[PDB]
Image (spheres, coloured by chain):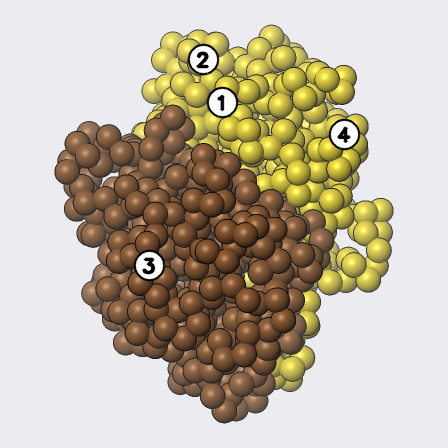
Chain colours: A brown, B yellow
Amino acid sequence: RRRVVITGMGMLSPLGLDVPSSWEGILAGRSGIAPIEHMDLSAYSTRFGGSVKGFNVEEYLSAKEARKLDLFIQYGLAASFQAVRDSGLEVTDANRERIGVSMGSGIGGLTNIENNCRSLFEQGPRRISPFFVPGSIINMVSGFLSIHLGLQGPNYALTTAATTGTHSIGMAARNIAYGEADVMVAGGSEMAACGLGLGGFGAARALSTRNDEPTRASRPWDRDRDGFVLSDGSGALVLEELEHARARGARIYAELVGFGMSGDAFHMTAPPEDGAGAARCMKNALRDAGLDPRQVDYINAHGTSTPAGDIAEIAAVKSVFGEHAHALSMSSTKSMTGHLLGAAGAVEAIFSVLALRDQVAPPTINLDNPDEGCDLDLVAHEAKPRKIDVALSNSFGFGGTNGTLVFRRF
Amino acid sequence: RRRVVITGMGMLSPLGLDVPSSWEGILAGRSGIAPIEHMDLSAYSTRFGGSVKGFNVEEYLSAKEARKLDLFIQYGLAASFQAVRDSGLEVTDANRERIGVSMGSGIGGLTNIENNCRSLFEQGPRRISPFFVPGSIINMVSGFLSIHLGLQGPNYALTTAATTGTHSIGMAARNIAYGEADVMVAGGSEMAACGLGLGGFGAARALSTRNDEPTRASRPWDRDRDGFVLSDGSGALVLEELEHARARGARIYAELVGFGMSGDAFHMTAPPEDGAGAARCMKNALRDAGLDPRQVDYINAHGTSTPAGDIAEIAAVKSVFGEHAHALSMSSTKSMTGHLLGAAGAVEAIFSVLALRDQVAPPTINLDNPDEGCDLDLVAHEAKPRKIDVALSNSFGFGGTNGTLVFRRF
Ligand SMILES: CC[C@H](NC(=O)c1cc[nH]n1)C(=O)O
Ligand SMILES: CC[C@H](NC(=O)c1cc[nH]n1)C(=O)O
C-alpha cells in the first residue's frame, strides 16, 4: 500500500528535555537515575528513579491551561509539540482532516487521582476538581494536542503498559498505510512516580531496591539485576506518507517498514522462559516488513532489568535470528533511562531511528557480569559505531502483550 | 481485502446479565436506572445510575482470581467469555496465534485505585496490594482473557472515553482485514460508580441530578435533559474473517463493513454546535463501507442526554443524510441503559447488530418534548419494527474523539 516515514521527533526523558540532549546522554553512557526529590520516600523500599529534571510547562502551555492537566498529559503535549515543530509541517484547511494523534499512557493521571482522592476522603466529594476527569483520562494528550493544533484526523489512545508507545506508533503507521491519515503524531507519556506508583510496583516486588547506587540499579542481563527502575517522560514521532513527505521536501529520518504483535497467553507479570511470544512478535514484524532475520543489524531491547524478562528476551532473539543472533547488536537503553512504561516504546523508537541516522548502537551500561546464556553482542558499557540498515524496537508488557517496530534507513 | 462478520456477542448491562435479557429490556422500553445501593451517596448531587444487578463473578472466575481484579476487569471478562461461548469457536494450536483481544475501558480501575489510596493515606505504602497494578490497568481485560483462553494474537486496549468500545471494535476489524488476525474479541467495560467517578462527573456538572425520578433522568433530545446518567457494564463481540467463519459453519449475526474516525479539534467536553466532526466521522465510515448515506436505515446515536451534545448530533445527521435524514430511524438506547462510557460503544454495537437481526429500531424512551430542530424519527417511546439493511453506531468522546461503525445484514 503506502509507505510511512518519520519526519519529526520529540522527547522528555531522564537524560534531557529534548531529543538531541537525551541522545547525547545515551551515546555517552550517562545514567538518568537519581534519588527522587519531589516527594519524601524515606518509608519506601525504592527511593530513586528517572525524573524529568527542570521541566518548564510554560514553554508549551499557559499556567491556567497547565494547572488543569496531570503531568503525564503535560509531558505528552511537550514531546508532541517538539515533534510537530521538528517535522516542519504546516497544518492548513487543505490537510487538517488528514492529520491525527495516537498518544498513549500506561497508568495515566495517577498523581491527579491520588491528590483528588486525598480531598475526597478528608473533605468529601465537593472538593474534587471540576477538571479531574478531562485532566486525568489517558486520551486527553490526543484530545488537547488535536485542539491546540487543529488536528481533525483519527484521534485515539492505547494503554498497554510497556507496549503502549510501540502499539501507538504501529497502529498510527497502519492508519497512514490504510489511507485513514497522511500524518499521525504518535507515542506515549508517563508520570507514575507518586505514592501509588512506587508503592504499587514495590508491593509487586517489581522494582530494583539498590538505593545505595541508583545509577547501577538498571543492569539488563547482569547477574545481579533485581527489577526495573521507574522513570517518567514522553516520546512523540511525526509519521507521514512518503509521497506526502517528499512533496513538501520534508527531512526524512528513516522509514517505518514493519509492525508486529503477539500475546504470550502465559502469565500477567512473567514471560515464558523461552520468550516464545516475543519470538512470534519479532517474526510478525519482520514478515510485515518483508525482511529476513539476517537483514537486522540493531535491536533496541525491552531489557527492563528483571530476572525472568531479560533472559526470556535472549532466548527469543536466539530462536528468531539463529546464527545471525551473534552478528547483530542488541542493547537496552533502559540501562541509562530506566523504564518509562507507557513512554518506553516511544523514546526507544526515537533511539532506534537515531541509531540509523548516526550509525551507532547505544550501549547497555552496568553490564558487568552477563548472566548465563547472555553471550550476544549486548553493546556492554560503550556505544559501538557500526553499519545499521535495519533496527528493531521490542516492547513486552504486563499481560504478555508484545509489540515490535522495524525501522530502516530510507 | 478480507470481509469481517460478527459470530458472537456478550454483555453485562443495567438491563441484564447477558445479551438476550438486555435486548428484551431494550425492545420493551425498560429503564435500567435506579438509586445506587452499593455506596452511600446522601452527600452527592447525583445518587442514581445504571448498575449491573446480581453479577456473580464465580460464574466466570474462581474467588481467589476474582479478588485480585477490579470490577471493570470482571465485567470485561464476563462479556468476553459470553461472546466466545456464543461464537462456538474452538481454540486449537492450529488457530490460537490468529485470535486476538481488544477490550478497552474509559476510566479503568477507579474503585481499586480509590481503595488502595485509602490504605496508602491511613497506613502508608506497605498496605498497597501486590496485585494493585496488574488488577487495575486497563489492558488486563485483554491480558487475563488471552491467558484464560490461550489467545496469542494481537493483544491491546483502547481508552477513548465514550468512543472506547467503538475504536476497540473498529481497530479489531482492521487487524482481521489486514491479515494480522482471523478472529478478535473486541469491546469495552466500565465500572466508574465510586466516589471519584460520581464526584468527578458531578464536579464537572456533567450528570443529570433528577434524583426524584431516576428512570426519567436520561432523556436524549428532550428539552428538559440535564446531563448524562453514569452506568456500568461491558460488551464484547467475536469479529471473524468471512471465509474462516463459513469454513466452520459459524452462525453469522451481521457484517461489519465500515469504520470511521475524526477529531473535533474544538473543546474537551463540548462539541461544535453544528457537529462538524461527527459529520466527517459518519462520512468516513460510509466511505470505508462503500455506502451512500441513502442506504442507511438505522442510527444507534451517541445521544447521552446533554444540552450541547444531543442537538450537535441532530445537526451532523441532517448535514450527512440531507432529505434521507427524515427517512432513516435514529434512537439513543442510553434513554434506557444510561451512559456506560468505555462500554457504551460495545453494547451499542450489539444493539445495532440485533436491530439488523430482529428488523426493529429500539426506542428513545423519555422523549416527551423534542427540543428545537429535533424533528427526525427518533423512535420516541416505543420500538419501531421496520426494514433495516444498514445500521450505524456513533460514539463522540471527551477530547472531541469520534468513531462510527457501519453494520450490514449479511
Ligand atoms: C510479561 C511482561 C514482560 N515480558 C517480558 O519481559 C518478556 C521477555 C520475553 N518475552 N516477554 C515481563 O516479563 O515483565
Ligand atoms: C466532545 C464530546 C461529546 N461530543 C458530542 O456529544 C458530539 C455531538 C456531536 N458531535 N460531538 C460531548 O459533547 O459530550
Indicate whether A136 appears above or below A322.
below
The residue at which mark 2 appears reads as B291
**Figure quadrant of the C terminus of chain B:** top right
Task: Give yes or no for contact between labels 2 and 3 (Cβ–Cβ under 8 Å).
Answer: no
Which mark is on residue A386? 3
Residue at mark 2 to residue at mark 3: CA–CA distance: 52 Å
Task: Give yes or no for contact between labels 3 and 1 (Cβ–Cβ under 8 Å).
Answer: no
**Kind of residue indicated by mark 4:** Leu
Q: Quadrant of residue A334?
A: bottom left
Q: Nearer the viewer, residue A36 or B15?
A: A36
Indicate whether B178 appears above or below B339.
above
Specify whether disc 4 shares its chain with disc 1.
yes
Q: Nearer the viewer, residue B126 or B280?
A: B126
Residue at mark 4 to residue at mark 1: CA–CA distance: 24 Å
Specify whether disc 4 shares its chain with disc 2.
yes
Judging from the image, what secondary structure is the residue with disc 3 in? loop
For the residues carrying marks 4 and 2, which lies nearer the camera in this image? 4
Residue at the image point whose x is 27% and y is 34% from the top: A242
Residue at the image point whose x is 32% and y is 54% from the top: A387
Residue at the image point whose x is 59% and y is 77% from the top: A223
The residue at which mark 4 appears reads as B89
Specify whether disc 3 shares its chain with disc 4.
no
Residue at the image point whose x is 57% and y is 50% from the top: A322
**Kind of residue indicated by mark 2:** Leu
Q: Dot 1: few (<14), some (14–19), or many (≥20) neighbours within 10 Å?
A: many
For the residues carrying marks 2 and 3, which lies nearer the camera in this image? 3
Q: Nearer the viewer, residue B92 or A163?
A: B92
For the residues carrying marks 3 and 4, which lies nearer the camera in this image? 3
- Beta carbon at label 2 within 8 Å of ligand 2: no
Chain label for disc 2? B
First in sequence, mark 4 or 2: give its number: 4
